[PDB]
Image (tube, rainbow, N blue to C red; front, side, top):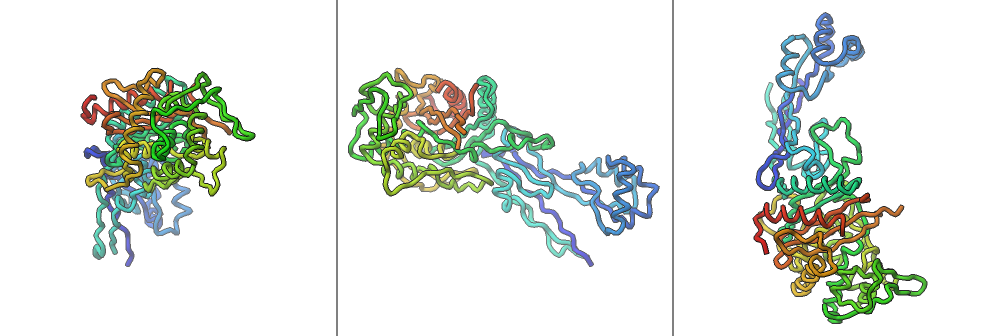
Length: 480
């Protein structure tokens, strides 16, 4: 008396509206009892042909495995083609009925959904992350069914497939139009912590993984870590405005675009300024300007805001090889390390962490935990920046996009947007174009990060413009 497992049907993955993203499809896996197959040798050439395998290769395989009470013949055969084998009616041939995944949206949501292995177990993305929820529990057969298989449970992602398609298309076009290698785009609901879209390029078809380059499989949004540069200056400014020592109309002299701190010299990307107000320091991305404010308030206040918005912290999503990056801490913050933290070369983050930090600022200073599954009851979340500072910083970022001298290519057709461009350094000196922002600026709903590796706020900003316009409309957000 022997036992054999009854495979359980893997749970359906849908997007947030019930659109199917991963579905367990019927297939048949033919095994055989060699010792039985060894009594029907004159059938072998027809079995071989019908199995795709080749006559002598097939005969060799069966002969050497003549002891084995059991061997597979083939996995994954369609159930109708698979009868064409049991239609030859060869002795020794027994069939198992099995499920295999199909991915109806294919390459569009490859990295977010991921895929299963040959054993129907999660290997990447959500398939891995919720493998236990989706897998259910195999059954048992001896005589009797000693245990009935329980089916895996349905899972509704936070992803909106309409926004994911728009993000996938617009990022793809931007990479060809800027001869760029790779890129990421993350869209978040700033109220719910939901990831509405996460697209990486290059992508792959999880329904055909034969010619699959490890480069295409890379979930860049959650894995690539970089120095966020000027895109974290809003968090430096949040610390400045919470200090009691700074208001937006305060002036800093940044002439002549350089600042010597001991042996080190801080050097601005544009060196045509003397007096700048705090908004101008952001618009110009003056490192001298943000450095002088950081020296006045202390790195500790900046470190604390960056920590509280989740920069360099575990996201809690449970995706495989999610990287945490690095928010370095000190007892004693010297001038050099204080400055480099304040203008964003003093830490490294992922696109997902950056978008989550921009969500907190956009959600009037309240952090909500990230979710890759549909949120029905919003968590309470944490007031990490006062609503008043958050409001002030939002208005500063709206000026960055829409003031004279600002990033005009991020302006969003129909709405007022807010955000900041940056030049990232990978973590031997690789460079990415960043844009981080949210909209609508006065009443934010969506936060977005665009990352474009090695293009060969002119590059990332127009992508943000186009994906944001489309996202706000698909979500029936009213024009301001």
